[PDB]
Image (spheres, rainbow, N blue to C red):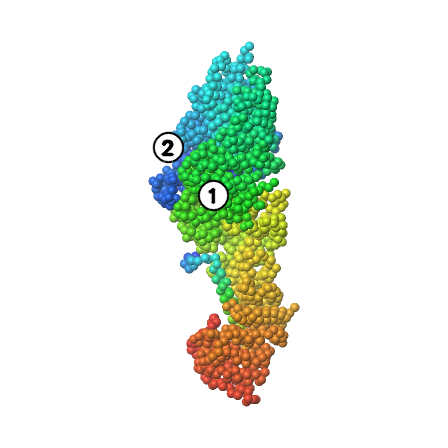
Amino acid sequence: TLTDRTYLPPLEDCLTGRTVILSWRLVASALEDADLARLTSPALSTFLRDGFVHELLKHPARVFEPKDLKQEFETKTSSIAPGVDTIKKDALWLADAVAINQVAALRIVLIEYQTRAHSHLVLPLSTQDVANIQEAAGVGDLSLLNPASAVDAETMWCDFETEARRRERILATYLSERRSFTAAVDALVTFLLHSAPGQHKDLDSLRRALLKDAFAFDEDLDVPDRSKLLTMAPTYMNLVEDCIARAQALPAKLGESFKTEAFELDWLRTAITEAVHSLSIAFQALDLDTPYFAPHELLSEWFELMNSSLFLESILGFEVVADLAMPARSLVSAICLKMLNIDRTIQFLHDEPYLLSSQTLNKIHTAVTNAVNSGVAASLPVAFAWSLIVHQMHLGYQERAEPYDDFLREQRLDNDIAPVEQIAMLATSRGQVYQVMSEMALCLGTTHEAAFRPAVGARARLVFQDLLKRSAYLIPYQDEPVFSLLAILATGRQYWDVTDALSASSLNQVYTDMLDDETLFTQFTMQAINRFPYEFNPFSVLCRVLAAALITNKDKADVVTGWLWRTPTLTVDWNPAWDRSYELCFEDENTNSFRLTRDVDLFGERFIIPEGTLGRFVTTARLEFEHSALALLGKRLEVKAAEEICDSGMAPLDVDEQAEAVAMLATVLRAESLKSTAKGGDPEAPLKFLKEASRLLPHNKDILTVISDTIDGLVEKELLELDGPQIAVLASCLQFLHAALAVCPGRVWAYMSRCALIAGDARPGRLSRITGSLDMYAERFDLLSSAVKLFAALIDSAACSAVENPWLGTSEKILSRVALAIAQAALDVYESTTTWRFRSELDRSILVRDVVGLMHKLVVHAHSHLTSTLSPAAAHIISSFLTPPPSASSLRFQPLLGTLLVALITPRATLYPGQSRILAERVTSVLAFCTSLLRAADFLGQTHIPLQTHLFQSACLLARLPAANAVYRAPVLELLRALVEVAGRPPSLLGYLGSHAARSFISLVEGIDKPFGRVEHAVVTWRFFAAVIRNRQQWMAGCLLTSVLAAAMERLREVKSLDVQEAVAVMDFVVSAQNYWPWTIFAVRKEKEVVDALRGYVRGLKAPGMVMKTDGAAAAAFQARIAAYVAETFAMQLYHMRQMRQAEKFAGELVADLDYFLREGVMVWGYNASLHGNFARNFAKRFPGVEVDDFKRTMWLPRELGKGYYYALEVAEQMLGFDAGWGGVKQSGFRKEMETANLNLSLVEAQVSLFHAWEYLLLELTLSLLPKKENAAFARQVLQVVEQCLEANQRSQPPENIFVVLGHARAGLALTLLQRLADANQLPRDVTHLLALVSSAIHAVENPFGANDLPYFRTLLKILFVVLRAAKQGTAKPVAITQQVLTILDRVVARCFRALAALVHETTAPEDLALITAILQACLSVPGIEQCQVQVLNIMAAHDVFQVAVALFSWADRLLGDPVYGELALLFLLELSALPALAEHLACDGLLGHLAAARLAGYMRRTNVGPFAENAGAARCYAIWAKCLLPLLLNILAALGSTVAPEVAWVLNQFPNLLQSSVERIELLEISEIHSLALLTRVLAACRAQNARDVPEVTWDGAKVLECVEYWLRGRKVLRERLVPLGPRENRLEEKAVGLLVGVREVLE
Amino acid sequence: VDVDTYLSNLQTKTTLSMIADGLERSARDFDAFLEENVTLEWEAQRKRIYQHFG
């Protein structure tokens, strides 16, 4: 029941790419890195929990051992997808050439096929790419580029698709898989054994499950079973034997064609690599059981193999494998030493061990003797240990002659000691063994240059520690062994290697053993304590390392402090000046003890050793008196810095001792601060350290002042003249400043303000002057890196300062100028990094990392109350980078190009993890720095940016970086997303990348993070694609579309199963591909429509009305945003369907899942302002200096919805953490409040987005529902929209920041949809409910037609107008509608009319006036007001509408242009006069006289008046005259016509020109003109009978009319000659024009 | 065959906001309905007054 189904997926899934094989490379990466997301991912978690994987990792040979499994291979390869032929052929060829099982070859070939794209991308650049990177570099200056013999990319691809290169890649993948499998098992071992505590919960569960299942190692038992874990050592030792055999013989069945120099080197390196990793596994297995022995048979076999291979030296003879030789030699020597465990060996034989088997003893002796006689140095430690063992054995038997006896007598060592003494002497002579031990320790240490990980390093150091332990007593105190042990413990570390990280308790044994076991503590620890200060190195390095190694150990946290404050012994050289201050005791001659007779004042409160103190002259003197050595060292440093000599004092500190002292002080201060800020530690520990260091010194000067004066004195001169020792002293002083920065920033900043190193206005700057072509070797690179890191920490402390007192003696100006000058210096360093000659690329890597990180922080806080604190430095940097001159641009970009090249040219390695981590760190830092710079350039508005082109040209390197390492995937695509986003506001991409390069990058990107299925990587790549579509990269998108489409569709098949975070991004990209590229996707959409529509229905009908009540209360934002995206997706497709005319059914089906949006979509109900208000209250009352709005993000980056959105939690975390209680207890406090508030506003933003998405959606749906049928659905729709507007327009209570658009779009949607239905004529008669509330809404606004709210007022009045229209289309009578309509129309018309007149007294205003008139008529036409005419008249009389209208129609005239205002005024009056009551009031107000005395009438009197006249004046005059008088004439004659007939006749006779002209051209609104004129004349003719005084003469020649109209009566064709309507003609205007003609003809007959 | 025709009549502009033009057309239709209704309303009132004396 242990199958390979999980270890390797089915063939079709492998080839299609649906599922990626979990190769050993990715497993080894995830294990070495211990990445939580990776290891705990479903795929890799299941892979690790597979019993079959367990079995093979237990038996490593099975992976590549040659067994006859034709059956399996044929069954897996058969019956599936074309292409299986080549895969099967290559697999069989590999199985036969390498002589392995067929399944292994098959999976190797599948790995190669899947990584085809990576392999093509990693190959060297082509000619086009080379030219692009050259153009990016520039002409002005050492790029160290690749040769130009590279062929064109086309030829490279055509060679890549051949069989030879495919087979070479398959062999490379096989070798890489060997290496990676061994490395993965090693990493798994050390992850199970010595994982650090505090590990994540799921990761700890995975570790425990692995242990229990694969090893029966259940921690749930007091003593778990370790058998299956100890079984590893011998299996992997046999494997190492097999590997050393392989390294000497190449595959036989392979052809010499494949056997090339490169392949031979690859094979040998692979063998050495798997040997190293197997040895690491074995050493861990043997390290688990520290105190017990190992079996003697295994030791015999191992040492026999050693003798045969000279401890792996037979394969490490070549030079190209030295990088793998030093590590392997260290590890094999250490595992031999381990097997011996001399401590317990020599403990046993004086008090089954391998000593009881003379066979094993003979094996060990012959192996050691051969390795010694040969003469290689890697065997010296083992030989020395064995020599000591044999020495003790010799003593043991010599004390018996008065099984190991058999061995001693076989080797004739019974009665002579010189055979072993010779080996011992040669091992210890000249410190050879000690020097190689130091080297092994360096490669096995915690530094970044170590070959193995830190943990393996600590255990490997333990073995050598035990060797030195038991050898200490028999060899006197010497420089070689003490320095060897110092190198063992320190491992060449520095101040920056200090940290409070909690590692496995087992891993600090190498350090605690110094104070736990007796031998070491007594012989070396106490000895160095005794020799200090005479020997400064022994004690200095010890304290420096232990203070850092005991940071987290609480029991031993006080030993360093007690030694420094309370040292029992002291040792110093004797100055003749003290010859008169002592006297011998005369007890023993050799003891040479003595006693002081005076007060010896060293440096002659001061440092004095009192009188009568004991001492001894060993060769120098030692006094055993209790005192504080810390104050002593502080005073010595003070003295040597002041250059004050003291003849009667002790010897001064030399340059080397000075540097070491400063370094130790800095390190101890850092450690004290670190464990003081830790929970429970005395917070005043660093201050007490500073005080005790300032004790017995000048009253007001402190150790900090000592360091300051030292720096000043040594920077007096320039840097290049200073020698190595002084440069190291300066580096130590900078490290001390960095250490002190945490506890006393004020002092450090106050000093930096006037430091010469930093550039200033007074002097240019010494640090700025050491730029050039000098070599950055250790002496100077230490100083440089220390300065850069101090500057970075300074920037950090400046950005993390929200506000006896830490910040004393400094001010805003100090911070600002220091930051500006620090930025200048960092820029100078970043520039000079190009030409400098570093000791190695790792130093360059570290330096570039640090400086780029500093500048990146500066850019980050560039991004506003306390931004000014460091804004000038950020401005300087961004200006230097975004708009520099050409030479400047090239020299500023060169480091980035070099970084990319180094990134993807450096080969991948399973060892030296520190180097790889630092290189990846600098890579990611430069990528994120470029990204932030592009964001800043896009935001601030600088368009011409050179970095743009430099990156577009370097895309050749960016697209290939992900192929070299997967960790670069995320930052690379963030940077490229930004690169195309800043440019979208067009550039070419393939022109730089290339056809083949772009296609390979496409395929590598395809199937986002398929092995691990992570969220962040997925999100980044999908947002990358979406932005790619949104910045109009029209070509690359079109190319990549052709199975990423199917990938997205399959991702969306089960949205409920996948996370919401994943979904929002994927569907954002789907929207971005649909909106911008509709035709390509709509076909594919048709293809997947059934499935996709199903899923969308589900998600949209989930309709969680109360998100916050349901479990997903904080996940409401992602829910709302994905809902909005679904809406935006379906909307545009249904609109295209409308255009396609096949929507009648699709809309009817879609309308059934809109309930979610109906309930709370248009409404933005859920804001809960109260919470934001209380948050503001708290932050404001607790912090007077800073206010709530000071944390508003500036949209510097593309604002990301998530844990932090409106408020920048990222920076608050560090700024507001300085104060206690911010975090609180049990996740209660202000941080929680900010999180909840920014989430509420996140979903509020998504809510506004949904408002817009639904504004889109509903419209084309309503338009697709125009057909008569299914009236219930559209009734529901209009009902719901009026409801949403009703409850949203009022009590909105929003922020008045982004609400401006809502206020208008709401009314827009309302009026649009209501008019759409009005066109359908299917609205109900009862609209009074909404009418009352809309009147209330119009009354709510505070200023009518205010400048700010004018658009809103216009739209609301339009809504009221259309609602009145709909209302009067009803039969209320065969709360009442009448009174409501009356009151609302009264108020609105009166107020608006008179206020508009007021302002327009002296364009928007007359347009709104026309609308007001329209509203007046629309409400007058209501069936229910004809019976209340009296009330309309009453309230139109209360307000003097009549008078103001009559006043302003004659607004402005000249006296013997066009009347617009007059037109509208008399239109208003006519519509008031529509019914006879107001008409009678106008008739009784002498309106006729008022308009006749006005000069608009004078203009009407002239002869140029015409319907289609030449000037707008005359046309306006025709229209106004006709409208204003003629219908008004008949309306007023309706009431008491007999009385006012005189006035109508007089106004008609006053202007005869129009009367004549009209009838002449009748011999088109002239129709209604003559209609009204004929009616008026015909009625007044009859009225004329009673009185001749009234209507004296008609003066109308209507005789022509009965002939004119009759000529156009019967001509259908003739009738459409001179008809031109101002309004749209559209079934014909004829239909009604001829109707008017008919109406007029009859009456006058 | 329909996809090819739609491609042949494809406007080279943003296809997302093609309904904003329709919303503006709906505003123009609002204006047209205003004109229609007011015109016909007081024309019908004039016809009423015409039949009254007639």
Q: Regarding mark 1 in the picture, which secondary structure is present there?
A: loop
**Residue A259, percent from left and from top:** 37, 32
Label disc, if present, on residue A599 of the rendered structure: none
Q: Nearer the viewer, residue A315 or A709?
A: A709
- Residue where numbered disc 1 is placed: A762
Mark 2 neighbour density, 10 Å: few (under 14) some (14–19) many (20 or more): few
Residue farthest toward the right in the current orientation of the protein: A1375
> Is residue A709 in view from this perspective?
yes
Counting residues from the N terminus, which is met first, the one under dot 2 or under dot 1? 2
Q: Position of residue A1314 (x, y in %)?
A: 55, 65
Judging depth in this view, the residue of A1198 and A701 nearest the camera is A701
Residue identifier under label 2: A261
Residue type at mark 1: give it.
Answer: Ala
Are there few (<14), some (14-19), or many (20+) residues within 10 Å of tag 1? few
Q: Nearer the viewer, residue A750 or A114?
A: A750
Residue at 61% of width from left, 48% of height from top? A1183
Q: Horizontally, is A261 left or right of A1468 in the view?
A: left
Q: Which numbered disc, 2 or 1, marks the residue closer to the eye?
A: 1
Residue A462, x across and y down, in percent? 53, 27
Residue A907 in the image, given as x and y percentages of width and height: 43, 36
Identify the chain of the residue marked 2, using the numbered disc in the image.
A
Q: Amino acid at mark 2?
A: Glu
- Separation of marks 2 and 1 at Cα, in angstroms: 62 Å
